[PDB]
Image (cartoon, rainbow, N blue to C red; front, top):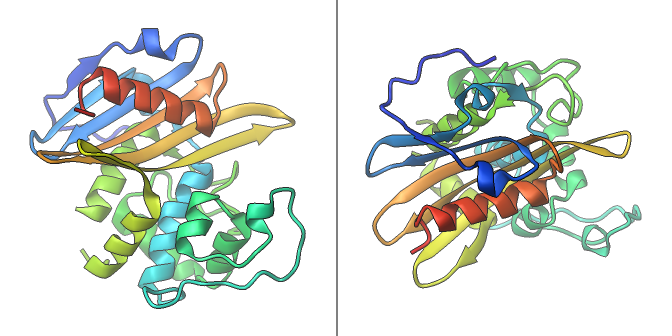
Length: 244
């Protein structure tokens, strides 16, 4: 588990109603208040594979290492057929992130030296920092991070040696929704084991006209999909008044 003390007078939450038959946790952090809000704190410290939420980090490393940049983040399709036509075409960072296009992020990852990743995960305090065989190590494999860490680590990364332009391009790629009241950013992740949803994530942040909130939902049981984790996140954010 993640055992490092949280030195914050955080607000305990009971979001059991919204979670329903799902198990997991929800963590939020307000920048302006310097305050965490946690549903199921013990569970929030349990480490799980990040699955595609790690594409946030692969994108950042890709930018930082100049594998991709603001003028050009395009990668050509090699004509391999996938079951979603959104994957069967050239991509840029925005479309790759939006459609969670594995081959795009795999190509980035295949260009990253293991020593560089190890250094970044150390600096970032990214969970167990366990790169294992270092192939698709973020997908139901060696690398594990807790829900509480997902918030702390993302917030700290974005809020160091990563450039402002890298952070801006990454942020633009994660934008899901914008209206008059808020902008919502985030990334889903889903672990499937032998057809069963086993691990669901939505990790993101909300910018309002008065504050910025980092958040993460993880689902460990019930219907633990990334899609469900996003729905629950959005329900909790609304119910807590963050979206007005």
